[PDB]
Amino acid sequence: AALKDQLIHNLLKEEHVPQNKITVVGVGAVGMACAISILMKDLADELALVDVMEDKLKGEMMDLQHGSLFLRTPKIVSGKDYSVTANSKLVIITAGARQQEGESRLNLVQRNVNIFKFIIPNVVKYSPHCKLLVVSNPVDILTYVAWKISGFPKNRVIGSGCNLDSARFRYLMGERLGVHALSCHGWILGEHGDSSVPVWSGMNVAGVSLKTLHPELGTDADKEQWKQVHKQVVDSAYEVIKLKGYTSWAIGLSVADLAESIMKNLRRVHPISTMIKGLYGIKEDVFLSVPCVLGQNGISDVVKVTLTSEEEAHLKKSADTLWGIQKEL
Amino acid sequence: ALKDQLIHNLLKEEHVPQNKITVVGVGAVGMACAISILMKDLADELALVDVMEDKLKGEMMDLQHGSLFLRTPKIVSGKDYSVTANSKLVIITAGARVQRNVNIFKFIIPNVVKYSPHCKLLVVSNPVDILTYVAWKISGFPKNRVIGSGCNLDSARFRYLMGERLGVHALSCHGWILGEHGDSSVPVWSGMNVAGVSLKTLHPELGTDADKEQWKQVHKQVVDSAYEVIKLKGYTSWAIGLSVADLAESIMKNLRRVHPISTMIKGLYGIKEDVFLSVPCVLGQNGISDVVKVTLTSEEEAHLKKSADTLWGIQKELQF
Amino acid sequence: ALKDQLIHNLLKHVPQNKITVVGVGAVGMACAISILMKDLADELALVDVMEDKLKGEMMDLQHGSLFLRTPKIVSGKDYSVTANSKLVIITAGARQQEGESRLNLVQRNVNIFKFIIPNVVKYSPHCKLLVVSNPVDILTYVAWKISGFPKNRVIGSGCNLDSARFRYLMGERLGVHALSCHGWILGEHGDSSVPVWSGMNVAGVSLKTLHPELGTDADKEQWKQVHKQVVDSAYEVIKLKGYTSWAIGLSVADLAESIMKNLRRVHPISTMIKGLYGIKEDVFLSVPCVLGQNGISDVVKVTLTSEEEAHLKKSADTLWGIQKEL
Amino acid sequence: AALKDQLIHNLLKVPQNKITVVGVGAVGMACAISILMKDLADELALVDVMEDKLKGEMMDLQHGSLFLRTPKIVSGKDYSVTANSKLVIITAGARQQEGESRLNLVQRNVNIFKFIIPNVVKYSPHCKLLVVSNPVDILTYVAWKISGFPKNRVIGSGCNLDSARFRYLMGERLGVHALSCHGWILGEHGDSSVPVWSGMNVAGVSLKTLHPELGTDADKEQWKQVHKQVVDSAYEVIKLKGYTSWAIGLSVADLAESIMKNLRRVHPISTMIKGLYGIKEDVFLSVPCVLGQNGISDVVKVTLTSEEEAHLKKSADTLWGIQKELQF
Ligand SMILES: NC(=O)C1=CN([C@@H]2O[C@H](COP(=O)(O)OP(=O)(O)OC[C@H]3O[C@@H](n4cnc5c(N)ncnc54)[C@H](O)[C@@H]3O)[C@@H](O)[C@H]2O)CC=C1
Ligand SMILES: NC(=O)C1=CN([C@@H]2O[C@H](COP(=O)(O)OP(=O)(O)OC[C@H]3O[C@@H](n4cnc5c(N)ncnc54)[C@H](O)[C@@H]3O)[C@@H](O)[C@H]2O)CC=C1
Ligand SMILES: NC(=O)C1=CN([C@@H]2O[C@H](COP(=O)(O)OP(=O)(O)OC[C@H]3O[C@@H](n4cnc5c(N)ncnc54)[C@H](O)[C@@H]3O)[C@@H](O)[C@H]2O)CC=C1
Ligand SMILES: NC(=O)C1=CN([C@@H]2O[C@H](COP(=O)(O)OP(=O)(O)OC[C@H]3O[C@@H](n4cnc5c(N)ncnc54)[C@H](O)[C@@H]3O)[C@@H](O)[C@H]2O)CC=C1
């Protein structure tokens, strides 16, 4: 008989019920950066990949499968049909058009809204209890779209948002100050995009307020021009796009950070995109980034940041920008 | 200045990296190696080198933007190999995708060796066995410090495929692909086992044409795998990145694990020429310190001699 | 109230990857710290009868929360804290005095299991039960009979540790890491364990092929003394520090990892072997088992020499002799 | 030939990331297991005066080698096993109160450090020295004076665990993970430590701005009792289980990670603070310190109230007072 039966006595007929399954929609540059970061952080016991082109999809799956010896995720699967995503805890959406050199994320909206009308109903059919983590751009507006299409409560529809902007800001802050980004605390809120809002009043190392030490922090009168650090954050993706054509590694690591807080129910605070109506002075159904408590139920809580009136005004302008696109959909 | 208002410096520090790694070539393979090494915390400094200077700065910046999520505090890049100085390990992934990559290595290797005279050289560029030889000749390093990624990946693929057929994890499926990376590689059917159970003793037709289960086709699938993935997505990157990081881990942590990697094998296995082939090698902080002597069948042994002769035939035609 | 000034609550907790440890002694806490540092659980629950020591171990772990990724640690003498565990690890009971056989602990620990196990089942009726308490093979059988669980879900830590010890000693003799030295110790976790000399190999190279007298009394290199060292290891360490903890901690966390991540790795662990290897009784002992999210789904059929086979049926005989009395 | 030579052809005839733990008690072995499970070392050495216990602990760890990525674990009462360590962690000594000030009791652990520290220096002269034994601020000073090391290479664990406990307690009250709560306990380890109310925050939101009574007796939420609770937590755990081990071991492994990976994270740890914060004596107090491969290279200058400043100055004076009476 077969070698497998010569070698192995089967004791147990098992139907596969996945316990810690994550799906990545889209095996482009971002989706595969998300995939490898999730795999190398041991967050899922099953990873499912979905996309619309079957060759690319099978190719990426096999390339990951070939490294199984080096991973601790035993089941990696893929298909064009969303049945392969069934019963995911977390579904990460990365499908969509990306920026050309110099193009605004907001110029992607018509193309990717239409894509979400195809994707989101399919996701929700097969993982009705999942958390949705939207990465595709413009991420704030597409989290809104995923919310309206899915019918999920707002705690379960999350945009990757400014987790990455805040990481970029902290890295640049640490380079100037000579400490690790981990030890530099500062928050970028609002749109993941040109209208993001640096919260100068909250920046600190070891609880020492930087704006107290350096009162011109964040103003145009500042001899050190710390405002150009936030400008570098705004410009960073256009700079990397100009240089290598796209961005991938940093967002993949940022998404895997968020995925860890969800899958392990850490209730860590992250600046991510959520439905902010009734807070921070905002009256419309806009999604933008504020500090959110993130765990196994998604966003359970929002932190109420004490913005200066000018920081509050920048945040309102960010909301108004997003609502100006949102109202046309 | 905010820095001085906030921080009182108590010590003048010279940057002397203690666990530095360099990756040469930031293509699909090099960046897969880079992200794997970063996510395994194997270096305190990562250096990147390429000739495409825009691509190089963009890749470096993209990794840097993820520092908050990593525990590698310094990531640097440049076309000038001064950025690679004092690396413990230098990984070569540059090149087309033989004579084209020899000509490249003629510029790369002397630059690497100038700035990190004591490093281990890990060659991934293809054809990996021939270019490890080239790197060895050009560097002047002793053979323990020149390593080809070789059949480490081939063996991982083999173990994945064996596991999917047997219903167990690749980790629990043991099997060795030796010799040349790619077409002429050698599946050592006699060593294949789960839990120390010899699959060839259990299933005597293992590895033969008369095998009703066609296990020989699993080797063909390993041989063919890079071509099938290239046909489907255009190149391979993730599996090789992870296997290079596995090697890097054994080197950086002095683990003395056994891997099937490409080493200068003259004087062993009946081989009489200066060729690099994969055999099981003990890998640690001095590179390859010891070679395991596998008991090969008479024509497993003949097949491995054929690879030697094949590789030697190409090496004789090299200009450098 | 500061919390409400700081935090707008949006949303009114079922743990998804919970692990319980019963017995927060030397072994239990080694298992706990090892599982915590491997990020295998989203909730860890601890149970003991000594309520003060229980609360103190819990608090000491909790104080390290900043450095961990397991956000909830709970404890109590009441087993309600353990509800909805995927995995429950039994490390409670009497341990060996210097020179004492593990089999001598059986009467005391059967008694203890009679209260423990029904309370575990009560709160986590679908968990996998990983028994560590000694004698581990007989107590896995006991846990199975008391719990009513199917055999796939009652696991004894068994010879995972013996084989790890064996591979460390082999690697030290061969100059390579334990990971690259392969070798299986089967049967009783104790004096009657069985080294499978025919499977010991590096890179698929059988040592017995180079050295057919390996492991036998005719071996000038005395490789049989390596197995003796494995047999004696627990006794030597008890004599030296009074107990063993760290290695079994790590071995249990290895097993936990295969279970919690559904790895289907093969481990030498204690299972109901009736009708394999020629055995006709309800004995538990270690053979190579495929370990995943449903526990033990498959057993590898190892081909033993006649002597290895005889030694395993003697190990089997030595057990059961005790089981039948209970 | 021998089996090994039949199997393996030797082709080729100094550890790079070695760590030593001195004292294999409750604290020392928690440090060891945490450091092993974080893959920070290529070699781990253990030293104690109890030779049986030492061999037993070493063997127990070795038996777990298969499950680790640290390939060499060594032990001995002779310090030759510690040679070439990057980091040496001192956990040896009598168990004593965090703030212990009584001279007879202090001097007992000073005497132990007189035997340990020169032997540590003998074999790892370039190491960083990490002192955990109590009283930690005084014994870090003693280790510095006996070792002859520059101050950047002598580190007291100080208030590093205190601040982690404080962040745990903050998170339990606020419903977030300790990682997302920020707060700093500084100064002299023990009853005299200084909770810096001004820096406590979540997401950069100052709790003291939202709750101006934070840290006063009139505060109806009694946040000042959270500091008392930190200061008393070790004693409460001792009362319950007889000693403490797991949290300190984790916090020491976190420091070691910063050192071994050259991370330059900021930790509240005890450093030779003369010349800063108005302090004029050779004392060790916890301040936010940048910790990397060369130890403590930089300190954050925290803006303190006049009273917080006075507290630190008085800690300096009383530590210096004790130190003057020590014999070594
Ligand atoms: N911080 C953030 O939120 C960032 C989000 N990014 C966005 O991520 C998305 C994907 O970027 P990349 O992966 O680099 O792009 P890519 O070109 O590499 O891949 C596009 C992906 O969308 C998938 N897709 C599915 N359906 C369609 C469709 N009808 N048309 C086009 N594509 C489809 C496509 O098959 C492919 O998987 C873009 O919207 C980017 O703007 C880019 C980087 C970071
Ligand atoms: N198992 C193995 O050994 C494998 C080896 N592989 C080989 O890896 C190599 C690279 O593959 P890819 O990454 O996909 O190719 P790629 O085209 O993505 O990247 C090649 C990189 O080399 C760079 N390069 C070229 N010349 C120089 C130079 N003189 N100095 C520095 N950099 C230079 C080039 O700019 C480019 O960024 C090829 O030889 C592949 O065949 C492919 C995958 C597996
Ligand atoms: N490889 C293996 O299988 C290993 C098995 N070991 C066994 O592990 C068990 C415990 O060893 P140690 O931790 O060192 O002993 P320990 O004395 O340190 O702890 C035992 C713990 O069990 C607790 N306990 C006793 N009765 C109950 C009860 N009814 N309910 C809950 N808890 C209870 C007891 O209070 C104590 O905290 C012994 O049976 C050992 O023989 C020791 C090491 C290896
Ligand atoms: N938060 C902190 O900073 C903590 C510091 N702690 C202190 O850490 C120290 C040790 O505590 P425990 O581990 O619980 O005590 P322990 O009694 O369990 O271990 C102390 C060890 O030091 C060893 N020892 C004594 N003298 C020497 C010597 N000359 N050379 C080598 N070894 C020696 C002793 O043999 C013993 O193995 C005490 O000073 C404690 O008060 C306790 C816990 C936390």
Image: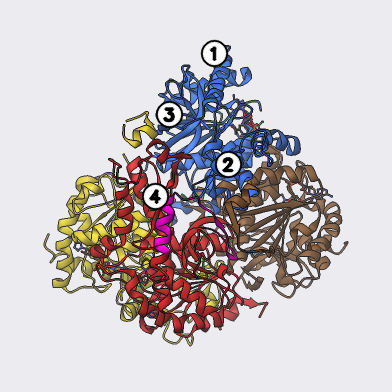
Chain colours: A brown, B blue, C red, D yellow
**Location of residue B318 in the rendering, given as x and y in whole percent from the top left corner:** 57, 13
Q: Is mark 4 within 8 Å of ligand 3?
A: no
Q: Nearer the viewer, residue D54 or B278?
A: B278
Given the image, on which type of amino acid does mark 2 rest? Ala
Letter of the chain that mark 4 sits on in the rendering: C
User: For mark 3, does the 10 Å Cα neighbourhood hold few (<14), some (14 to 19), or many (20 or more) residues?
Assistant: many
Whole-number angstrom distance, CA of label 4 to CA of label 2: 22 Å
> Callout 3: helix, strand or loop?
helix
User: For mark 4, does the 10 Å Cα neighbourhood hold few (<14), some (14 to 19), or many (20 or more) residues?
Assistant: many
Letter of the chain that mark 3 sits on in the rendering: B
* Residue visible at 40% across and 68% down in the picture: C319
Mark 3 vs mark 1: in front: 3
Mark 2 vs mark 1: in front: 2
Residue B320, labelled with which disc? 1
Q: Nearer the viewer, residue B241 or B72?
A: B241
Q: Which residue lies under the disc numbered 4? A: C167
* Residue visible at 38% across and 71% down in the picture: C134
Please provide the residue range marked out in magenta.
C289-316
Whole-number angstrom distance, CA of label 3 to CA of label 4: 28 Å
Question: Is residue C129 found left or right of A121 in the rendered image?
Answer: left
Q: Which residue lies under the disc numbered 3? A: B145
> Callout 2: helix, strand or loop?
helix
**Location of residue C309 in the rendering, given as x and y in whole percent from the top left corner:** 44, 54
Q: Quadrant of ligand 4?
A: bottom left
Is there CB contact under 8 Å for labels 3 and 1?
no
Among numbered discs 2 and 1, the one appearing first in the sequence = 2
**Location of residue A318 in the rendering, given as x and y in whole percent from the top left corner:** 73, 61
> Which residue is farthest left?
D327
Residue B111 vs B4, above or below: the answer is: above
> Callout 4: helix, strand or loop?
helix
